[PDB]
Image: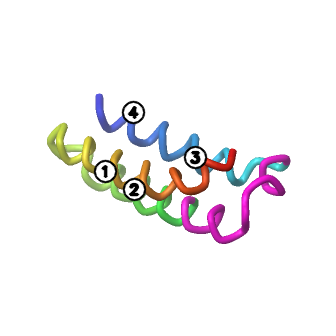
Amino acid sequence: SAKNALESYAFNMKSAVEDEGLKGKISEADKKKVLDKCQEVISWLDANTLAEKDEFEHKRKELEQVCNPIISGL
């Protein structure tokens, strides 16, 4: 269930930056970029549930790279 993993992961990063406390711990730009990216994958997840595992696996890598610069300061 790489789809479930991906969406939860994207939800998690999105929730973390958009968290009412972490919202002042991360910079607006990082918060924005990861949220937008999380929305990108999340809206894609909803569209490509039939994707292969590697599609999500790569999407995970993508999402990780967007949140990574933000998570490294969180």
First along the sequence among labels 4 and 2: 4
Q: Do the residues labelled 4 and 2 touch (CB within 8 Å)?
A: no
Q: On the rendered structure, is 50 left or right of 16?
A: left
Query: Mark 3: which amino acid?
Result: Met
Residue tagged 4: 5
Query: Mark 1: which amino acid?
Result: Lys
Between the residue at mark 2 and the residue at mark 3, the CA separation in whole angstroms equals: 12 Å
First along the sequence among labels 3 and 1: 3
Say which of marks 2 and 3 sits in front: 3
Q: Residues within 10 Å of mark 2 (few under 14, many from 20)?
A: many
- Residue 45: x and y in percent read 34, 50
- The prevailing secondary structure element of the residues shown in magenta is helix
- Residue 22: x and y in percent read 78, 48
Residue tagged 1: 59
Q: Give the position of the N terminus as an image quadrant.
A: top left
Dot 1: element: helix
Q: On the rendered structure, is 22 left or right of 50?
A: right
Between the residue at mark 3 and the residue at mark 1, the CA separation in whole angstroms equals: 14 Å
Residue 49 occupies which quadrant of the picture?
Answer: top left
Residue 3's place in the image compared with 1, above or below, is below
First along the sequence among labels 1 and 4: 4
**The magenta stretch spans which residues?**
21-34
**What number of labels is visible?**
4
Q: Are marks 1 and 2 in contact (CB under 8 Å)?
A: yes
